[PDB]
Length: 145
Length: 145
Ligand code: HEM
Ligand code: HEM
Image (cartoon, rainbow over all chains, first blue to last red):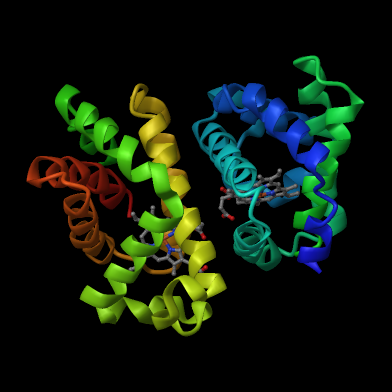
C-alpha cells in the first residue's frame, strides 16, 4: 500500500522535492511555524488536536508551538533523505504514522496540510509544479494512515 | 531544571558536539541501528518498552527497528541544530520529552543511552572528551523527564 504510493515518486518528482527542500529546509523554524500557523488559519478545526500547545494565536512567540513547528521539519528532512531507497522511505513513513494513527488523524485530515505547503512554497516562488510534487509525498504518508 | 541544564552547554562542549556529529551524523542509518542495538545488548531490560518493534535481534533486517533507528537520529540532528539558541534548544527538548514522559521513561532510564553513545563514538575514534560532551546534552533531556 505505502510501497505503491511511493511508486508515484518518479525521478522528476524526487528532483523537484529535493530542489525545493534545499530552500524550504534552510529555515526550519521560520518555515515550520509558517506551515503550522497557516494550517490553523485555513482550517481552524485542526486546532482541536493541539490543546496541549496552549494559546496558538501567539504563533512563533509560543514556546510549545515553536518547539512543535521546528520538530515537524525534521520528519520532512527524514523523508527527503530517504527518497532514493524505497525500502527505507517506507519504514520511516510507517514509523511516523504510528503516533498519528493513535491520535486518530485520518488520511483525509492529514491531507489538509497540502494547502499550507502550497502557500509556503509559493512564498519562496515555487509554483504548482512543486506543490504537486509535495502532494505526492504527502500521499505516501496518507497511504499509511 | 531544563533551563539550568541547557546553560551547562559551554562553548567547547558545543564545539565537540558539532565536530563529532559531523562524522556520526554522516551515516544515520548505520550509526542509528548501532546505537539502538547496543542499547538492547547492554541493557536487555529496556527491550520491554519496544514490544511493538518485534524481534529486535534481527537488527537491520527488522523493518520496524530500522525505521525507529533512522528516526532517532533526526532528533539528535534537531538538538545539534539548536545549539546556537538556548531558547529554541529548550522548547525542542521539552517537545521531545512529551512522548517519553507518556511512556514512563525516567531520567535514569533515558541515561542508559550514554553507554551506547560512548561506544559508537569510540568506534569512530572519538574518546572520553566527546562522550562526556554528549552526556551533557543527554542531561538536558534528562532534566525534562
Ligand atoms: C507534513 C505534515 C506533518 C508533519 C511532517 C508532522 C510531524 C510531526 C512530528 C515529527 C511530531 C512529533 C512526534 C509525534 O508525536 O508523532 C508530530 C506531532 C503531532 N502531530 Fe503531526 N505532522 C504533520 C501534520 C499533522 C497534522 C495535519 C495533524 C493534525 C491535523 C498533526 C497532529 C499532530 C499532533 C496533535 C501532534 C502532537 C503535538 C503535541 O502535543 O506536541 N500532524 N507531528
Ligand atoms: C539518544 C536518545 C534517544 C533519542 C534521540 C530518541 C528518539 C526518539 C524518537 C525521535 C522517537 C519517535 C517519536 C516519539 O514517538 O516520541 C522515539 C520513540 C520511542 N522512544 Fe525514544 N529516543 C532515545 C532514547 C530512548 C530510550 C533510552 C528509551 C527507552 C529506555 C526510549 C523509548 C522510546 C520508545 C518506546 C519509543 C517508541 C518506539 C516505537 O514504538 O516505534 N527512547 N524516541
